[PDB]
Structures are given as structure tokens and as C-alpha cells.
Image (tube, rainbow over all chains, first blue to last red; front, side):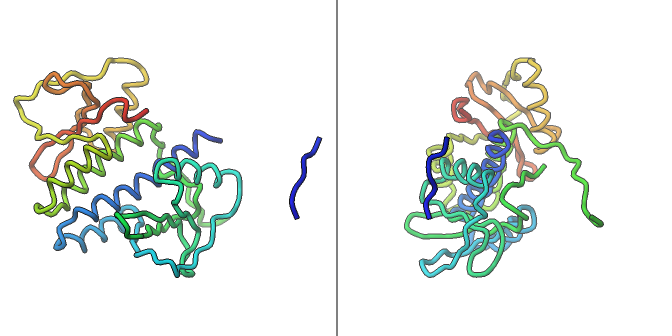
Length: 123
Length: 119
């Protein structure tokens, strides 16, 4: 069941940069937010970025992205910026989207993006 | 094949993506910031992002980026996305950096980012 010896990148940098920008936007704005503006922040991030934030638990089920060439690229550039431990998934606890894990100190979270597929760059 | 939308909006060059996103992160975190935690926010921006924030004043001096071909439309990507009055400078009050103005309501601000931070 193993294989044997036998005898695109620039776009994916833009896709990863845009997705990493959205995670850092979510994390930083949330972390330092006025509790009385937090509801407005979540609406702003959902309405403008299609972002929702979840706590991330050990018991979470997730499905990996389809294992295609572009995805492996995007995930590589995602990870070199946010960390190797970053989980990226097409689905968490049966809810589809582009999922990306992030941390605040020892707290785990998810951003879930309403996006179609991982290989997507908005104008 | 029906009801499939036609994409028409030019995408930004990589450097414009980075700079637009950094201003947006700075402006949005500040807009929603608890005054209790605001100093910690500024220090976090500096340490983790290389971002310094300043009030923008009428008494500021600033020099525009050099007038090359790449520069002028990267700037245009940036303005198209942040607002047409956005100032992009290589220098404010004789301090080098990538400087980008932004507003919250009737207040003007600068983001200053060290140039190497993009590389």
C-alpha cells in the first residue's frame, strides 16, 4: 500500500496571505476588544469576512482538505506563517467551510470561513 | 452553467495584499479596542507585527515613495482598497519606514511598518 521509485506557487502565496491575514485580524481584534463592542466585532467580521469564531476542543471532529497539489501549497504557506501545529480543515463537527485553528496563549480556537474552497483569492 | 457569476475585480499584488491587511488589522483592532487593554494592543502590534501607530497631524512632514512604475500601481491597489485619500510615504517626520495613513471617524492616524517586515 506504499508507492515505489519509478524510472502555481505565486497564486498560493496570495491565497495563504489572505487567509493568514483574516486569522490575525480575528485573533488580534478579539483579544483586545472592549466587551461591549464584541458583538459588533463578530458581526463586522462575519458580514465583511465571512468569519465565525469557535472554541477549539480536543474532542472536535474535523475533515482534512482534499489532498490536491494546490491545497498542499496553500497549507504549506499557511503553516510557515501561523505555525506548523496549525490545523486546516474543510469541515469541523460536521460544519463545512475553510477551517483554520489559532491560539491565544493556551486557548484553542477556530475561525470558520464561509468560503467555497481553499484555493480562492478575493478581489 | 446557469446563474454562475462573472468575476471582474482585479486582485492585488502580493505587497499590496500585505500592506492593506496590516492597515486593516491595525485599524480594526484599534476601533474595537478596550481602553483598558489599548497599550497592550499597541505593544503587541509592535512586537509581533513590527507596526507602530501614531496620530497623524497637520504639522507632519512626509516624502512620497520614489516615482517608479511598480510603486505607482501598487499604491493604486492600496488606495483602491483603503480609500482614495490614503497617504503612502517612505518617510514621516524624517523617520524611514512604509507609512500608511488611515482614519477612525474624524481622527487621522499613521501606520509605520519597517520595510524589511514585508520580506
